[PDB]
Length: 181
Ligand SMILES: [Mn+2]
Ligand SMILES: [Mn+2]
View 1 (cartoon, rainbow, N blue to C red):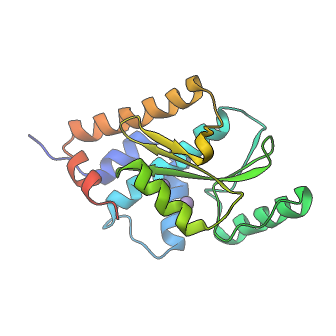
View 2 (tube, protein in one colour):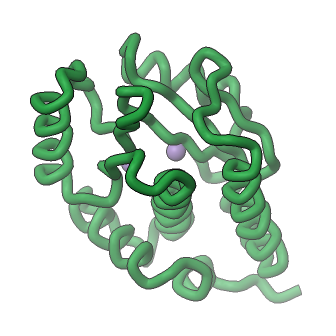
View 3 (cartoon, helix red, strand yellow):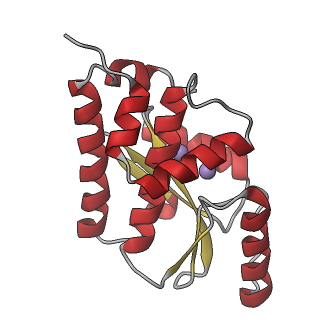
């Protein structure tokens, strides 16, 4: 069976805006997508999920993810000044204007409860909401509050399942799943 290249797959699978934002993220962090290509795919996947999460309720969420880091912090600080929300210690992915809280979106190939616990230990915040997705349909969220309804989250889960299936068809899934740290 042919083993495809992950860079080929990423450039064929994600829309060009997502690919370009992922390229800029990796440049900002001094990473080379041509070598760390599983990470390139992971960054693209996380961007796509953040955008889908926002699109599930247009106008409800401010998007923080995808922006360069300086601009992202400028947006976080603006939200905090406007809404009175407490400033997060690490850059979150969205701000929810309805529930008045920042959100960390996780997408993982590891077990979602462990990943959830790791993220909650990292950000160390009593306000920021965490929502973890896997590629096989499992999810986990702060206080069992999943924010979006079943139809919206099913759309996200189906996209993730499709990505995993297309990776597997190209012989890419085994390495992509194994390489997460
Ligand atoms: Mn991020
Ligand atoms: Mn993640």
